[PDB]
Amino acid sequence: MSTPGAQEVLFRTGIAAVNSTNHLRVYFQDSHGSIRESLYESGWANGTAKNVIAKAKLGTPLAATSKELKNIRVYSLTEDNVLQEAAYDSGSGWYNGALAGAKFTVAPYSRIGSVFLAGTNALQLRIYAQKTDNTIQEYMWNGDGWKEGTNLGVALPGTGIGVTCWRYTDYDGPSIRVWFQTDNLKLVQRAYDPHTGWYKELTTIFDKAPPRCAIAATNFNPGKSSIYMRIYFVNSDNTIWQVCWDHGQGYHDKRTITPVIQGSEIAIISWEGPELRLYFQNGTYVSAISEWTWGKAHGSQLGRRALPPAE
Amino acid sequence: MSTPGAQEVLFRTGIAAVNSTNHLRVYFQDSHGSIRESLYESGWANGTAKNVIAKAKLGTPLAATSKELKNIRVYSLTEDNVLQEAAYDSGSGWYNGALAGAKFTVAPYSRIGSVFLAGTNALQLRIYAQKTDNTIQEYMWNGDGWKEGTNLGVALPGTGIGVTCWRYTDYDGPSIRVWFQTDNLKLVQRAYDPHTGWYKELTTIFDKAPPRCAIAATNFNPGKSSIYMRIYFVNSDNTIWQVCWDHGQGYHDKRTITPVIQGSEIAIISWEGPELRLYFQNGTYVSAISEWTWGKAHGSQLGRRALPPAE
Ligand SMILES: C[Se][C@H]1O[C@@H](C)[C@@H](O)[C@@H](O)[C@@H]1O
Ligand SMILES: C[Se][C@H]1O[C@@H](C)[C@@H](O)[C@@H](O)[C@@H]1O
Ligand SMILES: C[Se][C@H]1O[C@@H](C)[C@@H](O)[C@@H](O)[C@@H]1O
Ligand SMILES: C[Se][C@H]1O[C@@H](C)[C@@H](O)[C@@H](O)[C@@H]1O
Ligand SMILES: C[Se][C@H]1O[C@@H](C)[C@@H](O)[C@@H](O)[C@@H]1O
Ligand SMILES: C[Se][C@H]1O[C@@H](C)[C@@H](O)[C@@H](O)[C@@H]1O
Ligand SMILES: C[Se][C@H]1O[C@@H](C)[C@@H](O)[C@@H](O)[C@@H]1O
Ligand SMILES: C[Se][C@H]1O[C@@H](C)[C@@H](O)[C@@H](O)[C@@H]1O
Ligand SMILES: C[Se][C@H]1O[C@@H](C)[C@@H](O)[C@@H](O)[C@@H]1O
Ligand SMILES: C[Se][C@H]1O[C@@H](C)[C@@H](O)[C@@H](O)[C@@H]1O
Ligand SMILES: C[Se][C@H]1O[C@@H](C)[C@@H](O)[C@@H](O)[C@@H]1O
Ligand SMILES: C[Se][C@H]1O[C@@H](C)[C@@H](O)[C@@H](O)[C@@H]1O
């Protein structure tokens, strides 16, 4: 039970997504290795072979980040496991970013996380990937070329990488949180705040997760020394689980959210409300990408059953 | 928790295996796309970058078949999704078989099943794969070049393909059984016997399985209108399940066997005893291949924890 379009979507494809409020873009890999863009603009569209923005190694990790939908960056691996960047800016179309020119080689099993730094009109990027020594390496662009940032230490080979960024309204710089899996299979957090920089502490957010389980995170409603974060990962019950940080309660909830196929990748986006949108494969038309939604109006509800090009 | 060697094994690699009694060969894909051979000769060895027999598309299906260990054939897909064949004959070493020359193009998500026809000294091959119309196509070599055999009809896009072959001691030709998954997610059997040829009947062996779950089969103790078959697949509980055919009882048992990683591929071999050996990934050193064994002496027992090159 599939469709011609759904068959084009790679099984266990990497998934990434960006948005400006409820204006959405979702990136995935097709069965021939091309990275495609589906979009939501008061309705779903595209995701076809005419909507290719990049070509990457089969089974590549995918990450994306944006400033609204004015600047979009999509990260993947070349067949030589070099980090590369597909870039879009308003009124310039899609092009190759400078990242690949830096020739950052990572482990073949590396994932990728990516954020624009929040709370500034400047375009500042932090990318996170896994080197062949299994450490999680930050790579950065601040208008003075691509270079290595901070190394966050050793993770499980092939760990998922979740990352989110915001700016506290009472701080003068960005806060970054990065989640990954350690050798003991725990899910942990590294943290960056202004002034303190990277905290030394690793915080456990889940005791045991499947090896190389997908990890994805978002945040909403930043305020005065306050944030709200959601981290998603694929658990051993073949569902996405959610971990909640809420100002006033800290890390205080772990729940299953929705079923997925074995080994599904995941992507999360959000906007103020909060509105949450989760993307994953749950077996709809075998290989189509499905959507899960959260909003105040209706709470947890499945969304678009089969993203373009499935139907 | 991994090892340098284990890290070389592709996560969710295709797996195939051949044997002459307890002389074993196991094939898998490394993280750079090369197909490697590990062997058991009174002890496990090889599986290193010096033990490459082929190069294939990343995430390729793998199938293998042999006449004892005198003739071995290993099947995979090129980056253009053409069926290709790595071949070994005693005292000739490894080489490229003629299969790729036939330019059989299949669906990007195609699996592969392969057998030498049993009960004859002749070298006769039947390969099974999935075309872009999602039908399961037989391809054959009988000493008059590669050509298409019988088409077995429509299967779920990306179905596992299990196949086994024997000769009844009271028949003058080979019997073939092929298992795959249909659109309704059932696991079914197609059957070939001498004279009758391919039976029209599809036999359900399992009511519902995960989409594109791995499927692998073996047989032992052929006799007078009698056979014993074992079919393995990855079930929704992230374990390999076994389905038993036994002469006198028919299809009469379904059981879990052993845990695997989400989306593990599987391979099965056997020899008279019966002795069974199952290969799969269960998360040992994250990406190492593990072994499960069955014999009369000790019944169900885990075998080699981490195949070469893991340790
Ligand atoms: C009716 Se809720 C609506 O929200 C939009 C932003 C998209 O996520 C749609 O897929 C969804 O149905
Ligand atoms: C004209 Se719709 C436009 O939206 C931009 C933000 C990008 O996502 C483009 O790929 C897309 O074509
Ligand atoms: C000047 Se276009 C520039 O944009 C930056 C934000 C980075 O994405 C670079 O890789 C890209 O070339
Ligand atoms: C002085 Se560049 C600085 O930027 C911070 C926001 C973090 O990304 C650090 O890792 C980095 O060294
Ligand atoms: C000491 Se900074 C603090 O920041 C919060 C938003 C969470 O990330 C906590 O885990 C962390 O300890
Ligand atoms: C008020 Se707690 C509430 O927060 C929402 C944003 C979602 O994450 C829900 O799953 C959660 O229960
Ligand atoms: C001690 Se049972 C023995 O059987 C051999 C044929 C191999 O399968 C070994 O891995 C296994 O330990
Ligand atoms: C000398 Se061991 C020998 O065994 C053969 C049957 C093949 O498996 C070869 O690849 C291997 O080197
Ligand atoms: C004469 Se070598 C020959 O062996 C046959 C059994 C097939 O495997 C052919 O593809 C191969 O070239
Ligand atoms: C006459 Se060729 C014959 O061989 C049988 C054993 C089966 O493989 C059939 O599919 C094939 O047509
Ligand atoms: C009518 Se042939 C018979 O052969 C047995 C070995 C099994 O494959 C049965 O499912 C099949 O019906
Ligand atoms: C005697 Se039934 C017995 O047969 C063995 C070969 C294995 O398949 C076992 O799992 C099964 O219970």
Image (cartoon, coloured by chain):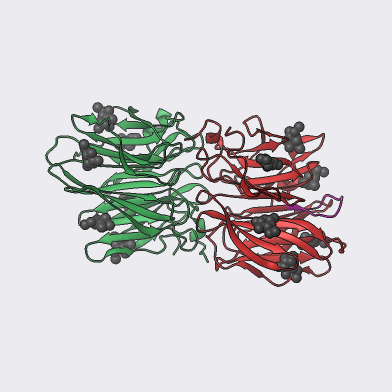
Chain colours: A green, B red
Q: Where A91 falls versus B211 (above or below)? A: above
Q: Nearer the viewer, residue A9 or B269?
A: B269
Q: Quadrant of the C terminus of chain B?
A: top right
Viewer can see residue A86: no
Q: Position of residue A252 (x, y in %)?
A: 25, 50
Q: How many marks?
A: 0
Q: Residue furthest front?
A: B297
Task: Write down which quadrant ligand 1 falls in.
Answer: bottom left
Answer above or below: position of A81 versus A270: above
Q: Nearer the viewer, residue A16 or B300?
A: B300
Q: Position of residue A27 (x, y in %)?
A: 39, 50
| Residue A55 in sight | yes
Residue B252: x %, y % from top left? 66, 67
Does B295 sit left or right of A240 as displayed? Answer: right
Secondary structure that dominates the magenta span: loop
- In percent of the image, x 79 and y 43: which residue is there? B71
Please provide percent x and percent y for residue B236. Answer: 50, 59
Q: Is residue B101 magenta?
A: no
Between A97 and B136, the residue placed more toward the observer is B136
Q: Which residues are magenta?
A: B115-125
Q: Quadrant of residue A260?
A: bottom left
